[PDB]
Length: 457
RNA sequence: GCCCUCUUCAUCUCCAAAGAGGGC
Ligand SMILES: Nc1ncnc2c1ncn2[C@@H]1O[C@H](C[C@@H](N)CC[C@H](N)C(=O)O)[C@@H](O)[C@H]1O
Image (tube, rainbow, N blue to C red; front, side):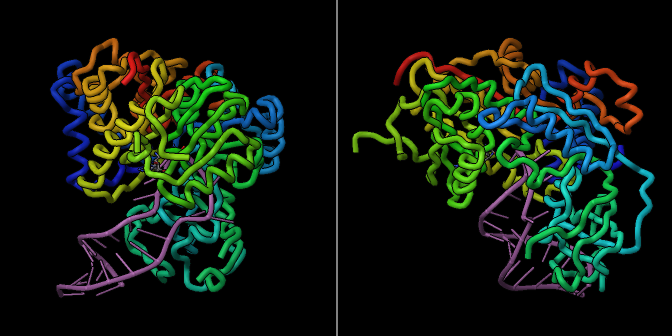
């Protein structure tokens, strides 16, 4: 609608096309209908999801208790403006907050600010512009003036640049907390008083009760279905959104092991675990590809966990909003070998009759369905299983999988439904039945696979 | 000032990158 397609290098944009126009997909659909769904996908990755999704930490407060407190917070932020807060009927701990946008009649100001590409995404998701996110502002920008915020999506603007002619995209207007001289540090930089997409700010709303998580990511731990008193492993876990979710589903009864290769990233897990009141979590900085111990705290012996979650590192191109990804084709393909190494460690560490859930935050066939076919061939002890709840679409063709196997996977296609232009007259002219499905389809690009280990090794 | 590479950290919701070297 409002934003152009995701700016991809000519090499990577065709690398995705080659996978989305494979012989398996263009035979089921049409050759003209296969490219239409691919170019529609490229147009949707630039836009934010039409819903804000929050996960209630049920170990410290109720869904009924946090929803009421969120209504109190939403009226303060929106100044009487009442946007509903739905509750997902399939995910008991997730609340849905519809996005108001895109607004297209916003008058642009002469005072400007450029922010980082990732900071620009958070603005489109309801965040304000804090101090370390501004990359450039107008020369002598007065503290307290209404300012036009733009996202440096190519990430090419140097810090403190007086001007910037490169590709920038309008994010809305707001009044600034600080001056340009004071910027070029923490605190509030630019309070978004008129964003293109309207959604609540969740910076420090209810740190012990909430966790802002995408719907397909909160669905992951539900699909994993941990049980109280089980030994669960989160191989790639930081910052621990799913790890804390798994601990909450077990009522903190059991053992949840969390790993990640970066020291500070692991510290975030420990803070989030303590902040949300989970004591069953134990986080370690460790290479998951080396987490298997043998004859001669990680590493662990094989067949040691009841369930294992591999939210593997990926190309991350199933992210929304994503208006520019300047990666190489080699950097996008950089994740396939590392995924297969982490997968091999999980299969060995999983107990017999254990459950393994594999998930990515990208859209590529080589990282989602091709890995499932590779796993079920290299690991005869594994067997694909149906998922509960089933929220996303079927698996994508091109990996030579069954129709019964594709029906068992959950791939979230942002191309599934058209982008809505939600103003406040639209919700008052809509039913709760339609918005629940829109939240299940207008999601980020995501993939979920679930296996079970038949025999031992 | 404009344009390029390269090294890592990074967007999987909210304090959001900073180095190296080239061309005009
Ligand atoms: N060899 C490794 N061992 C452990 N963790 C890794 C390894 N390589 C990458 N990672 C982590 O894997 C994560 C990739 C993410 N997709 C997982 C994030 C996490 N599931 C979340 O809820 O946000 C990153 O945080 C990486 O730091």
